[PDB]
Structure formats: structure tokens, C-alpha cells
Image 1: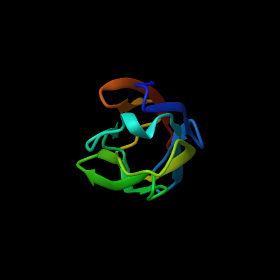
Image 2: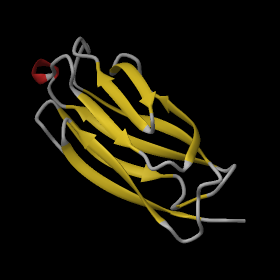
Image 3: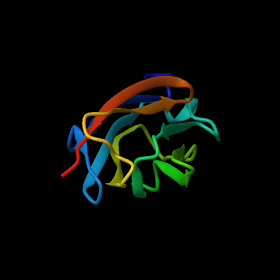
Image 4: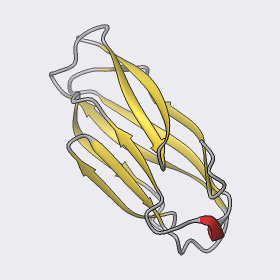
Amino acid sequence: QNDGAVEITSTTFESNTVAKGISNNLRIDYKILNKDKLKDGDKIVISLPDIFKDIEPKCHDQHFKDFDVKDGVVTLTFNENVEKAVTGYMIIRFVGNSNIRKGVSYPVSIDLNGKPSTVYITGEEY
């Protein structure tokens, strides 16, 4: 996922499993490669299945001018005024909800301006 303005270098969950009432964090490592190629509306979109309570993005507010959570879709909007090329990371904090079923593979899509990727986390019940 590299459009010349931005590269997503890594997308990793703290744990490969998710459970009701248990925290997991998604970490997204990125580089702003070329601030001059950024445009207002450039974004990372994370689409989640309905297995989370408490979706909370954490980011560098000079790299992302806004973030929004709506109906399981997290939008991170790049700051087109970022001062310079930079390496960073952001986190989506998650808590599982009671919809989680043991062994079920849940897709999480991470899209850099419609350049897509999918990672999978599996349900656990305790």
C-alpha cells in the first residue's frame, strides 16, 4: 500500500484473538513519503465487523488532521499541511463485544485511498 504520498509499512494486532470484554489494539505503521503529493481527503479507512465495543483511534494530530468512527468504519484523514516527510504509527484501541464466537475468522480491511488490505483476528470465548 504505497501511493507515492504515503506508505503503510505494517498492520498488526497486539493479539491474533479477540474476546468479549478484552482489549486488543491494531497498530498501523506508516510513512508520509512526500508531503507535496498529499491532498485534502487522502485517508486510511479501517472497516470492522460488528465485534467491538469502545473503538478509539489514537494518532499524531500533525499527521492526521481528523479521525472519525461511524458504524464500525474508522476514517483517518491525513493533514495535507504536514510540515515534512515523516515516519509514524497510530493505534485503534478495541474492546470485544458479546457477538464474538470462538474460532470465527473476522476480516479487518485497511484501505489507503482505495488500495486495500485485509488482516484476520479469530474469536475466543472464555
